[PDB]
Length: 220
Image (tube, rainbow, N blue to C red; front, side, top):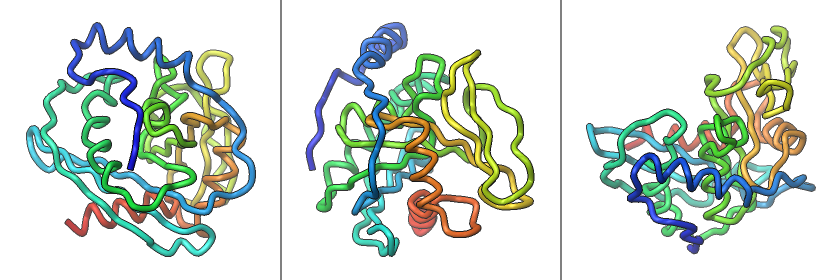
């Protein structure tokens, strides 16, 4: 399974920041229309001090049947720097990506995308490489400002950077904290909202793709 190596990974943090900027102009915040056939959930986890693990699961929509599950381990060499996290986890995910048999229609990551100091969260960065619509879903806020939406199923608020809408905050499950949805590449706020709603069972808290990938990560 293919991808486009837009740049090298072994960069100094200063250079990494410069790339992010270059890539952000390549981002296309474009409506996703209709429903995907296949969605992928991604879970990037770190068993060791410098050991990463990438698990990808490809569900079929609307059934959420698990068609495929791939995983790779890699050395995590790049230092942990908030806003530069993709340089740590990007490489390893790509190893897992290359092992996929089924081509996903939309990919959901555990992170953000547009909601990023430089509008290049994990979902955005990888969207550029894998060249398919992506979304970032986070169980906790990473970037941006919001008003807590009410404690009522499916309530929601916009997420902001200053005055610009950078994603949304959804109360997916009553009496639980909300999730944080930000578009990646070939994705806008509005479409990402709709899709993530479409990927969540009522009324669980976490979208199936990411719930399931975590479950598989756990299974290891």
